[PDB]
Image (spheres, rainbow, N blue to C red):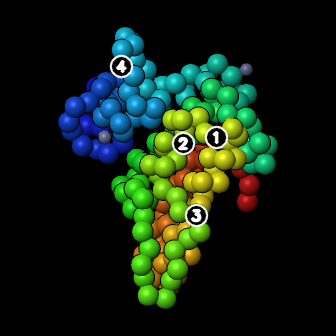
């Protein structure tokens, strides 16, 4: 197994996957690493199993269909993994905890949003469809773009949104287009 957490790339108290060489901190894994379960399989392994059980699940899909899916166990898992993939980028630090807004010439968003709030919402099964989760994730970056206006710091939102969108298209097998 790896000697650093797959998400934050730090050592510490790590839990090891039994089916692949990744390791995690307890709360870096999503969902949080389970109390017992020997053997234990990480989310990367669980996602791979879905695809192997139903190879046709990798054929292309329309985003509009994906968004209307109900949050059954498999879609819940895919959203958890997509959230995890965003936390894997170090620039997610800017969007993790609850923001505050006091900048000359700007007004804070009507509906603040951040990664830890989405994480909690997923944990508490607050989303009924994929659309709920995707809307909140996109709202994080849209709020950032609007607030920071022409400051170059706006680019961090563009950057992290691109990681989200690429991973969304991969995990949910969105039909490739020009
Ligand atoms: Zn970690
Ligand atoms: Zn694994
Ligand atoms: Zn199948």
Pointer 2 or 4: first along the chain: 4
Residue at (49, 49) in percent of width and height: 117
Q: Is residue 112 left or right of residue 135?
A: left
User: Which badge, 1 or 4, is on the more N-terminal residue?
Assistant: 4
- Give the label on residue 111, or none: 3
Q: Which mark is residue 127?
A: 1
Mark 2 or mark 4, which is nearer to you?
2
Which of discs 3 and 4 lies nearer the camera? The answer is 3
The residue at which mark 4 appears reads as: 35
Which numbered marker is on residue 121? 2
Q: Secondary structure at mark 1?
A: loop
- Of mark 3 and mark 4, the one earlier in the sequence is 4
- Which of disc 1 and disc 3 is earlier in sequence? 3
Q: Quadrant of residue 18?
A: top left
Circle 3 — which element? loop
Q: Of helix, strand and loop, which one carries label 4?
A: loop
Report how far apart the C-alphas of labels 1 and 4 lie in the structure.
24 Å
Looking at the image, the residue that sits furthest to the bottom is 105
The residue nearer to you, when weighing 140 against 5, is: 140
Q: Which residue is nearer to you in this view: 112 or 151?
A: 112
x and y percentages locating residue 49 in the rendered image: 56, 22
160, above or below 48, in the image: below
């Amino acid at each position: 197994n790896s000697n650093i957490c797959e998400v934050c790339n730090k050592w510490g108290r790590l839990f090891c996957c039994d089916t692949c060489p990744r390791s995690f901190h307890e709360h870096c894994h999503i969902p949080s690493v389970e109390a017992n379960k020997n053997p234990w399989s990480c989310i990367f392994c669980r996602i791979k199993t879905i695809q192997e059980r139903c190879p046709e699940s990798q054929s292309g899909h329309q985003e509009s269909e994906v968004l209307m899916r109900q949050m059954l166990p498999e879609e819940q898992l895919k959203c958890e993994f997509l959230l995890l993939k965003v936390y894997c980028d170090s620039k997610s630090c800017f969007f993790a905890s609850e923001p505050y807004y006091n900048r000359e010439g700007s007004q804070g968003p009507q509906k603040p949003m951040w990664l830890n709030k989405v994480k909690t919402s997923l944990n508490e099964q607050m989303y009924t469809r994929v659309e709920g989760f995707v809307q909140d994730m996109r709202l994080i970056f849209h709020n950032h773009k609007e607030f920071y206006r022409e400051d170059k710091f706006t680019r961090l939102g563009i950057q992290v949104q691109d990681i989200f969108e690429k991973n969304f298209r991969n995990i949910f097998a969105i039909q490739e287009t020009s």
